[PDB]
Length: 53
Length: 72
Length: 177
Image (cartoon, rainbow over all chains, first blue to last red; front, side, top):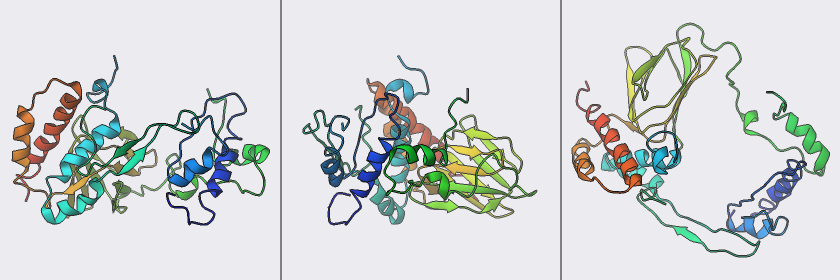
C-alpha cells in the first residue's frame, strides 16, 4: 500500500517476499526486487538492500 | 536489429501497442460512454530507480488521455 | 526436457525447507481457477463455454455454439470441437452467436485462445459495442492519420496501428442491420 495505517498488510507480504527470496535462490540466481507502494520500499530496503532496484 | 511484428521492430512492446489501440478506440465512442471510458484512460503513478539501496531519481506519470504514444 | 517439474503443490514442499513455519504456504492463481485446458470434457455437443474478457469488465461467461473472431489472417469461426488455437486478433468485430440473436462487439485487438477442451477465451483490452461507437469521428480520425507521415519509427508503428483500427471500424459501422 501507499498509506501506512493498514495494520499488518505491507509487512505481511514482506514476511512472504523474504520467504520466497529464501526459497528460489539456492543456486546463485539474479534477483531484482521491485515494490509498489510507499510502504514497500520503506520495508524492503530493511531486508533486501542490494537487490532492490 | 529485432525480429517480429511491426510494433516489435520499431521498439514498441505489445502492451504499448495494444493500449494504443485501446486508446484510440475509447475516443470514438459516444460521449455518454466516452466519459465513462475516460476514467480508465488516466495514468498517474511515479517510478524511481533505486541504485544503492538509498537513493535515485524519480519519474512522475500524469497522462490523462492514455499511454505515451511517443518513443520512450 | 522435463528436468524440473514445478507447480503449486511442488512450491509447498521446497518452501517448507527454507521458510519459517509460522507463515503458511502462500496461495497461487492456479488455485482460483476451476477450468483447466488439458482435461477432457465441457463441449457437450452444440455449445462450448466462451469467455469474453477485458481488463476492466467481463462481457460474457455464457455458452455459445459459435464465435466469430477477427484474426490477423481474417475473420475465423470457432465451432464446438474446434482445433486448439492461440489466435492473435487485429482490430475487428467479435460475434458471439448462440442462435438467431447476435451480440457483436468491436474489439481493440487482443488474443483469443481455443483450448484442448473446447473452451474459448477471448482476451481483448477495449470492447466497443457496435451501437455505442461514434460514427462521426471514425472518418475525421483517419484523415489526420493518413496524412501524418513522420520520420520516427515509433509513430510509424503507431500510425500504422492507428489507421488499421479506424479502417476496420468504418467497415463495421456501415452495413449493420
